[PDB]
Image (cartoon, coloured by chain):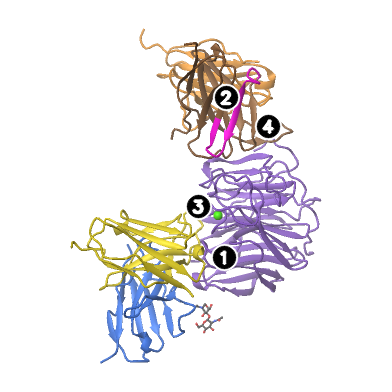
Amino acid sequence: EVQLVESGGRALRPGGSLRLSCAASGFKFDDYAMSWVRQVPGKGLEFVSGLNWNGDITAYTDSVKGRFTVSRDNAKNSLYLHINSPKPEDTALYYCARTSSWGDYTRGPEPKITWYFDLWGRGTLVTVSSA
Amino acid sequence: RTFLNLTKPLCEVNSWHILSAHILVTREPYLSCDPQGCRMFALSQGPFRALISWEMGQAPSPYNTRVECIGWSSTSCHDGISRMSICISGPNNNASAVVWYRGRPVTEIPSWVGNILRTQESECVCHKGICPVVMTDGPANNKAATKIIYFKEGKIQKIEELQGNAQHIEECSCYGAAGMIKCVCRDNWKGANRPIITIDPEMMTHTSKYLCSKILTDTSRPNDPTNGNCDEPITGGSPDPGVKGFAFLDGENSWLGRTISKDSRSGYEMLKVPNAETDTQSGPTSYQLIVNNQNWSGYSGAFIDYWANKECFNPCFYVELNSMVALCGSRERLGSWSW
Amino acid sequence: SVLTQPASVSGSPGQSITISCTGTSSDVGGYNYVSWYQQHPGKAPKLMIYDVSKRPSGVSNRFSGSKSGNTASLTISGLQAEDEADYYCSSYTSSSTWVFGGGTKLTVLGQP
Amino acid sequence: DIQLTQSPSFLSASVGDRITITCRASQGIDGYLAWYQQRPGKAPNLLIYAASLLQSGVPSRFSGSGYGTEFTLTISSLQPEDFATYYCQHLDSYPLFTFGPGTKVDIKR
Amino acid sequence: QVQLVQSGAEVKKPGSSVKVSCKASGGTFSSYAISWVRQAPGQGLEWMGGIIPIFGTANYAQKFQGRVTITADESTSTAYMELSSLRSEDTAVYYCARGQLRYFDWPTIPSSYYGMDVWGQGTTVTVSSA
Ligand SMILES: *[C@@H]1O[C@H](CO)[C@@H](O[C@@H]2O[C@H](CO)[C@@H](O)[C@H](O)[C@H]2NC(C)=O)[C@H](O)[C@H]1NC(C)=O
Ligand SMILES: [Ca+2]
């Protein structure tokens, strides 16, 4: 069936680099967008980054604009999120979410990126502490 | 008087010719033919968007105009006795299409995916009362459900799902010739080459494929490949996903219109690429510079005055800029005298 | 066949100077495809006038063009400051080839 | 720069009762809003999108309504599986896809 | 913003072959006709050749027929201009210019008026024996 599996998440120290991997099975990989959504163990979900099927359009939030890398490998059917320059505010659980669109009819040249998430995963933990 | 019959063929055209108490905010304007001549339709804002159709040349004023139906996406044409119009109104998730026939509503069609129902936003073609209309519902950057609805006297005779190798179908332009209708339009999701749909109202069927010409006719697009393919789409270009256009296909009598820039909607040119239907290594002949690269362009459509007093149909086109230009010429050949 | 220009013309500021370019009938007279270029030493030529009597993006109004028979005329009304340059006339021929004029040196003095 | 606050923050209701939740935004967002349910220690699952359209697999006892700044979600009959947290997400907020602060519902005492 | 960048100065021996490049700002020759002009030092200009890559049509001046060759590479949008059998009088400045094609038709006069509305900085070529 539809399944998303996350791996590679772990606690790390400031100034390090981490790679989070997402594997999808049970649907058409290249006909859907994919994103990551994080949630601290105390509060609600927060968007971080995402991309479309070919990677032409990529979205990063304000707080991770200069230190996050998002890529997808359709040949291996995988999604990769690279986190560099971590901060103690990046301790949370990450979920890999299959992302679709609604109401994306734009007459002008600029595409409309309206996204909502349907399929989720177990998520991986990322704790940043100076120890 | 009598229902229109697509029997006259589409003879060769060589060079295009100039054909084109206040105005309203008119956007998405196309052209539709009728026994009285040709009229221009546009969507005006007056939450209450409405179609307004006016005579050729005359400015849009509240004295010679008539409203067809209410909505934001629409299509309209004629069958020789009556005019059939289709509009889409309602919320985005609950869009409904209302059909008008001789100025009164006759049919309502509900949505089936509930994600912005849209129509071809051009003219339709009527053959012995059968007037196909292509509608699409779903994502505009992914797989969407495309259906074809056949109307007659403002009533439904057949709704059939899309066939063929087409993957995404929006905002199509249809022209009739020899009893068969050909529709060319935009692949907004993946392809950079326009699909083509062949509709036969005799057997009441259609088929879909792509254009085999190597000259791509969408914006944005990459550089023209050596071997244009008409089974699988060609992907590339940024950032624009696509633009509505048109293409006339009569073997050696073929015309493709595209923007000058490969990334932006600036300028408009045409090419007479021989055998646009099947040839994969085809290359263009007659060039004509319609709109220079300096100013902006927009949606381009095709229309034919089938009620002409000729043995042909004499196709014609329109390109937007804002204002728009409606152009078509005769067998007179290109030169320093053409514009 | 090569078009001919007078030689070199000049005048005082505040006057109008006319440069003439004549050729044959198969290149200049037949087609309204005569252009005018100005070039400064060490600088690439600039399309001063295109389509006989039309101006590109910008270009001061002082430049004007006219045609009569096989003669193309460029008129500068009120030569202001620094129009001193090499001016060239170009025509499009029936053989899909461009022909360039000999060239005219317009020189402006700076002090008596 | 569109706010998103949802109420009530906490609500205790018995099984099979009328329960509704309201998500509010600073300005009109059309129908660009979705609702997500997350069970204690479970991955969140989408309930409704476009503020009125139910998902294919979700039960038919979840209803959504609203068009503008106020959106309402109603559970037809509470179930043992219905004890979870709820979030409202904005769609046309590239690239700040805002989520709701969170509403938690528990068994009444 | 530079539109076209050619290369730079060069000195070549007599009797050899010279090759000059013209690259557009964008890597696409959609409908632009690329012309090549020559200017002798302090005398004037001299139209030398022209190419239309979309129709693949190459035209040369009467004097330079059989000596100048112009080719186009749409992979890199590069126009190559080549002379063979260089003489001592070949020292000049070569420019590449661009124009907008208006119409094209084989029976009537092809290669419509496209002008020289965009130019380049120029390439100096000097022929000498030392
Ligand atoms: C879409 O709009 C139609 C009406 O245009 C809705 O259909 C009506 O629904 C109400 C109850 O919701 C019924 O009492 C009416 O009898 C229905 N009318 C018709 C003609 O069917 C429909 O429910 C709306 N759909 C959504 C998802 O909001
Ligand atoms: Ca496309």
Residue E110's disc is: 4
Q: Are marks 2 and 1 in contact (CB under 8 Å)?
A: no
Q: Are marks 1 and 3 in contact (CB under 8 Å)?
A: no
Q: Which residues are magenta?
A: E62-79
The residue under label 2 is E82
The residue under label 3 is B240
The amino acid on which the numbered mark 1 sits, given as a three-letter code, is Arg
Viewer-side label of 2, 1? 2
Chain that appears orange:
C
Q: Nearer the viewer, residue D94 or C47?
A: D94
Q: Nearer the viewer, residue B37 or B163?
A: B163
Q: Position of residue A102 (x, y in %)?
A: 47, 67
Mark 1 and mark 4: Cα distance apart in space = 43 Å
- Which color was chain B given? purple
The amino acid on which the numbered mark 2 sits, given as a three-letter code, is Glu
- Which color was chain A given? yellow
Q: Does E50 sit left or right of E21 as displayed?
A: right
The amino acid on which the numbered mark 3 sits, given as a three-letter code, is Asp
Image quarter for ligand 2 equals bottom right
Viewer-side label of 1, 3? 3
Mark 4 and mark 3: Cα distance apart in space = 33 Å
Q: Position of residue B166 (x, y in %)?
A: 62, 61
Viewer-side label of 3, 2? 2
Q: Are marks 2 and 4 in contact (CB under 8 Å)?
A: no
Q: Is residue E72 magenta?
A: yes
Question: Label 4 is found on which chain of the structure?
Answer: E
Looking at the rendered image, the quarter that the N terminus of chain B falls into is bottom right
- Which color was chain D given? blue
Question: Label 1 is found on which chain of the structure?
Answer: B
Check the image and report above or below for A32 versus B259.
Answer: below
Mark 2 and mark 1: Cα distance apart in space = 55 Å
The amino acid on which the numbered mark 4 sits, given as a three-letter code, is Pro
